[PDB]
Length: 232
Image 1 (cartoon, helix red, strand yellow):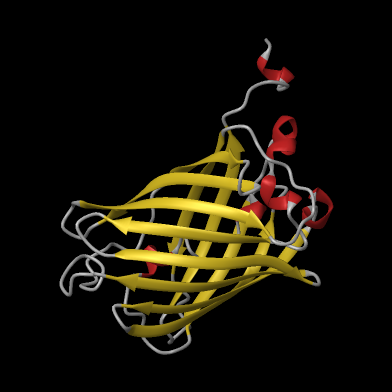
Image 2 (cartoon, rainbow, N blue to C red):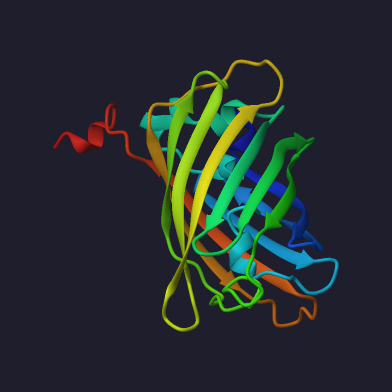
């Protein structure tokens, strides 16, 4: 629940990936401040060079750090499933290109929130925008649309990421998401709402390994009932 997220929380991220047979690993570390909706992480490709553009991994690499406004806190499934955690699964369909399938478990290991991911990508084009590394190193702002999945006792989400391509075009990545709690504990199943997400990508000038520094802000919105500041 909310009590685990009231301060600054250390984060660890571990990804094992395989895209068109190219195997790679990513590790990240940082901290999250759910009260302000802020995440700061640094990621390293521990196997060498990354075979895909860093931006294509941003969404895969802990929505429990979203800032839910006071009047919406009963719609925060992610924190309600902690510390035991949840499984997050996605299909990410890159328009005119391949598909990522991801499975992650997000849970606390003591004081640390840990996101452990497996990623499998198939059907990518050798000189498409992904395997051809034609995406700009930046990120746009997007909304993540959430709805309850009573039958799986969790949530579904959908959104479309727009990756800037170096030639001025846009590479769409359609996201279909499911989250299911780990274990049988009670959870909060929300009304429809969304997460507004901003991200800033940068580099550590003293880092020689292939890496990504990330700052992210995430707030929940889309429900108005109970927000008295909106009356007048």
